[PDB]
Image (cartoon, rainbow, N blue to C red; front, side, top):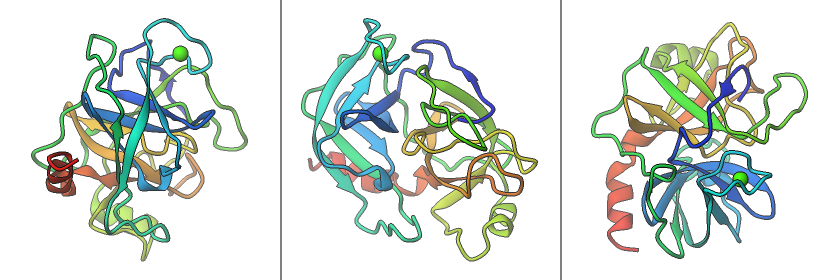
Length: 223
Ligand SMILES: [Ca+2]
């Protein structure tokens, strides 16, 4: 997250870190057994880390649970990032508590102009590199479909939305991929892509979770 703030330990209790020896993407806990992330975050050998604040210090509230299954969307296209969504099943259910909690899936899609909370352990620099240890947060508004399409001509599908600030300075970034975009208390987006981070006229692009709720529900009813 570039231009964000330190969230505060465990104040985003549905945020997970995906670890394959190191943190490599975020995700969102949607119930005690299942995490939503980005398909472009797929790796074999994923451990889900819940209850994290500092990802480099064991502070006492974590749960580390291996994935048993990952399910990339059946129509994911890694070239365009259309349908950039994945489900990860935990080997054992998380113990839900004040610091480890699920986020609701949406009933309706979010509205342009809505301010959403984006979070993660990704790079904090637009130019260069610096990865935080503690979880960072950003409030960013959803942009209109037409502004998003103007920013990325020929690249935005109906399964994507843009959020952020066209003047630059505030965005998600590498390492935030797969993490949540929460709007009015619902998981509306997944950190997916963008050209650089926090650059002028290049806002973040997010997977539009409300298009996937029937897939998510049928998949979790069957696995
Ligand atoms: Ca930790």
